[PDB]
Amino acid sequence: GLPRKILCAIAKKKGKCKGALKLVCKC
Image 1 (tube, rainbow, N blue to C red):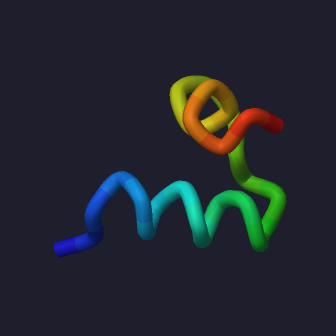
Image 2 (cartoon, rainbow, N blue to C red):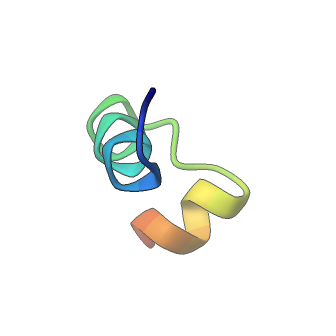
């Protein structure tokens, strides 16, 4: 599967760092 770090990396790159991913990716 995809680790939260990888999810955050993808979200960070794609600009999909929202919600919890916003907190983690710090967008």
